[PDB]
Amino acid sequence: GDFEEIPEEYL
Amino acid sequence: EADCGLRPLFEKKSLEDKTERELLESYID
Amino acid sequence: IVEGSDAEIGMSPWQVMLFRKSPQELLCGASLISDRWVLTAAHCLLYPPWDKNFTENDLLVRIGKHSRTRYERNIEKISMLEKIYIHPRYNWRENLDRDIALMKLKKPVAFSDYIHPVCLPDRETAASLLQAGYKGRVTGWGNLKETGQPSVLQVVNLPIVERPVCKDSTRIRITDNMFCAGYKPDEGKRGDACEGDSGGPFVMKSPFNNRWYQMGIVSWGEGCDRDGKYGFYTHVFRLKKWIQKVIDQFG
Ligand SMILES: NC(=[NH2+])c1ccc(CNC(=O)[C@@H]2CCCN2C(=O)[C@H](N)Cc2ccccc2)cc1
Ligand code: NA
Ligand code: NA
Image 1 (cartoon, rainbow over the protein chains, first blue to last red):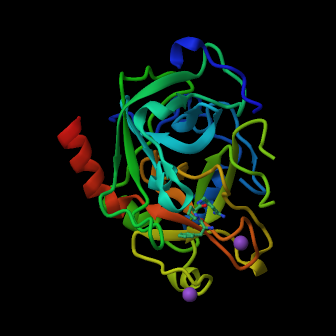
Image 2 (cartoon, rainbow over the protein chains, first blue to last red):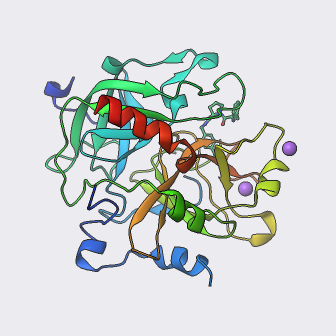
């Protein structure tokens, strides 16, 4: 829940 | 890898981390 | 990691974080063993008593990290999984015997000051270092207590324990594919891996060639840092023939 979001390119 | 296990920020520039000597001292004598 | 300390930058450049795609969370630790192969614990990927069975598309590998939750722009590298390989005789039904899995990445990761593979032991280094009393180092972003969540990667050095003391500390059946580490209650010092540290490396620095070798994988424990209990680690050297077969057959 506390994770900063990763660049969308990786999902 | 030929270079495996050699850390760029420690072994590769001959720097030691703060607690690796604790391991060395345990490999007795 | 319980009773450990914050890592220095670049101290464990083979440390890998296994990350769940949705909900976005830490799943496990792991280690980099080449530019395309990552080593972890099988229970990180498959554990039917807990309804755990991840597939490649469920996960990401994050390499070069220090901060647990932050996206470390220009430092970490995030990689997709090509394929997972679990030991065919991994014993999830009983005692996590042969708790080891490999992951191949879709593309090779770029090495850097923060990203660098660890060595796997050959028979002689293992014979020389895997001795009661000799200390290794375990790293991870798992729980700080049995019952957070650290801000950054944690590290703790722990001595290997004699196999009879390992055996006498638990009712679980121990095998030659496992070893245990930790301080005894009369030794004063403490420390242990814990939930979330699963799959991360137990490493030792060889005094012969000053290289770091991965001797264990964080596997299991009863509670964390309890007196008279020890952490159990997969014995990497004993399962190395499987490791090499996979990489030799699949690249
Ligand atoms: N060093 C430690 N204190 C420690 C503790 C826990 C973990 C994470 N590993 C686990 O949580 C594993 C997953 C299956 C149950 N489990 C456990 O560690 C169980 N608590 C003990 C157990 C039960 C059945 C078979 C083998 C071991 C990793 C390290
Ligand atoms: Na026992
Ligand atoms: Na203990």
